[PDB]
Length: 160
Length: 161
Image (tube, each protein chain N blue to C red):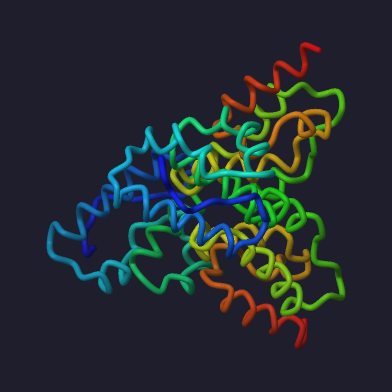
């Protein structure tokens, strides 16, 4: 990283970050720079607020892998996973909200979580306890295997 | 299952269920019974309440494995996962409850979940939002990789803030 053209000013756009990190991942094995010596001179590739950031976070930067992970973590703005779970369990299904809109609001938060963390069974387990008592008296967790099954059966209780 | 000695009357005991399911799984392909020919004649292995039960649940038993799953689900009762998640997220960390005891009770609930479902990263994600604001001002999720890290740092804020 002695004369790398690539730079990053701290713009919080996902693809800006992915191209810069892709660009520096280039350089590290352009000239044969170490893991230690890549994390050595990473500051030289930052300017503006990317350096205000790195100067504040160079202490979790134990590894080159964690430093790259930190760049994606801060500069690709996401609702953090822990904030997603809290918001997931904060609003139960009231007596007036239909089943379709309730599942939409819950699947919206679940889609922000890492793909492949929870399967559809686990996601139903996270959801089922918040389902209103109006629907749970007629449908049982072991009877539903997919969100489609939950919606399909839940739409029938809404007809009568 | 034309002349199987093994039977099950519907007693809701974990160990009764495990021996019955183990015995029929044994029998099923010592004699080479299909998965679909086992689900055909599974009714012959039930008596009493277990047959009144099977007639109520053999609609949801599309496959042989789902029939076994129904037996464990119904006659080996466990605390449902959805009830565990619900009560896990029901009480935040109050201002005077220390982090150590709060984390213990919360991780106790996570231990009730199926073994191997969540790794420590996900379990930290489930917990972190419940931590009191006076710890979260000083600790950031990206700083914690293990409950060990969270507890160690959390003990420092209660020593002197």
